[PDB]
Each structure stands twice: as structure tokens, then as C-alpha cells.
Amino acid sequence: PPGPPGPPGPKGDPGPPGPPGPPG
Amino acid sequence: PPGPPGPPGPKGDPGPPGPPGPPG
Amino acid sequence: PPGPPGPPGPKGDPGPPGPPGPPG
């Protein structure tokens, strides 16, 4: 029989920078 | 006999966008 | 003989939240 599925892959990168702060 | 575990899975998605920046 | 290697593992988890955006 084929072996078990391998381990979970590496977690993704940190997400994009957030939006600019609100306008004064 | 059973085969060995498969390779590591693919890489994950980028994380969520970050928070809005500080007020000016 | 031992069977074929298993499939690739699950896709990795999403990364963490990104950093704060620029000052408003």
C-alpha cells in the first residue's frame, strides 16, 4: 500500500501591510 | 509493506492584511 | 517491497497578520 500523506506544508508569509491611518 | 510518508505539503497562503496605521 | 511514498501533505496554514500600515 501507498504510505501516509506527508506532513502539513510550511505556514504562509506574514500578510500585506495594513492601510494608512485615517485622515485628520 | 506500507510505503513511507509523502513529502511536505505546499506552502500556505499569505496572512491577513495588517491593521490600519496610526493617525497623523 | 515497501509500497510507494504517500501523497504530498496538506497545504500549509495561512501566515500571521501583516504589520501596521503607514502613519495617516
Image: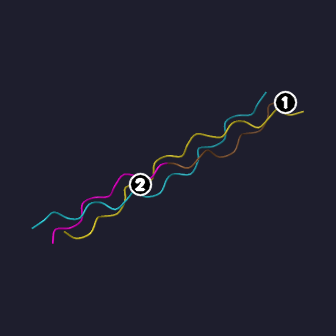
Chain colours: A cyan, B brown, C yellow
> What numbered label is drawn on residue B1?
1
Q: Which chain does tag 1 point to? A: B
Q: Which chain does tag 2 point to? A: C
Density class for disc 2 (Cα within 10 Å; few <14, some 14-19, many ≥20) is: some
**Mark whose residue sits in front, 2 or 1:** 2
* Relative depth, front residue between B2 and C12: C12
What is the x, y in percent for residue B17? 34, 55
Q: Is residue A17 above or below residue B10?
A: below
Density class for disc 1 (Cα within 10 Å; few <14, some 14-19, many ≥20) is: few
What is the x, y in percent for residue C10? 58, 39
Residue shown at 30%/64% (left/top)?
Answer: C20
Asked whether the beta carbons under mark 2 and mark 1 sit within 8 Å of each other, the answer is no
Q: As shown in the figure, which amino acid type bears the numbered disc 1?
A: Pro
Quadrant hosting residue C9: top right
In the figure, is residue A6 to the left or right of A16? right
What residue is shown with label 2? C16
Quadrant hosting residue C19: bottom left
* Relative depth, front residue between C19 and A4: C19
Total numbered labels placed on residues in the image: 2
Q: As shown in the figure, which amino acid type bears the numbered disc 2?
A: Pro
Residue shown at 30%/60% (left/top)?
Answer: A18
The region drawn magenta spans B13-24
What is the x, y in percent for residue A12? 49, 53
